[PDB]
Amino acid sequence: CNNYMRNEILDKLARNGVFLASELEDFECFLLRLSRIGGVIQDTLPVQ
Amino acid sequence: LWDLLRQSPQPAQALLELLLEEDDGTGLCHWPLQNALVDLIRKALRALQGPDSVPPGVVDAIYGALRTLRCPAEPLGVELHLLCEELLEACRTEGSPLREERLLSCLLHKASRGLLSLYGHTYAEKV
Image 1 (tube, helix red, strand yellow):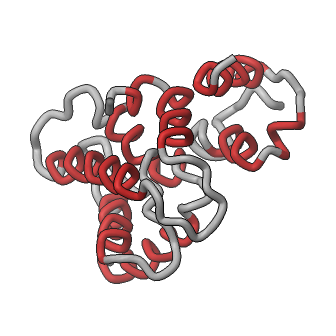
Image 2 (image 1 turned 180 degrees about the horizontal axis):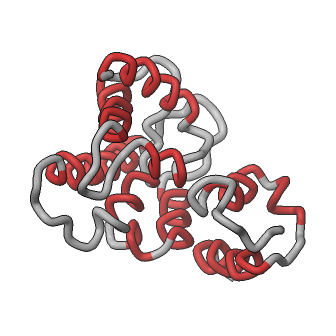
């Protein structure tokens, strides 16, 4: 789709864990995924 | 069109990425957009610097405008270190919605680690 739709939709993919590593390599997408949630970590996260 | 700052990090992120173009070089094109969004955050904060109640945006739109600011590394003007010290000496405060802390939380990008170092220098200055 478009760009914002992609950010929040892969965000859907990731708030639960669609394990696709392309973004995690993708410097813009990787930085977004790690830190853009407020840093690369969380409290007791959905990525245990 | 500054309303996508709050609207979504999907939206604020997409606007910051596409409006100024992703130029991977020394080109200074469309720096006014990042500077103006930086200033929008700067207003939202400098105004939050007292006891006034923060309306909607100093909690999402100030953040989006700031995320739209590539006030980058390399030798820059007084604004980069000034806003760096702002976020940092802001992390030396509380009560309204700004700091260097959530700043660092949601402000890890290509044009930001060097500004973070500048924030270190000016934050030693503030402390």
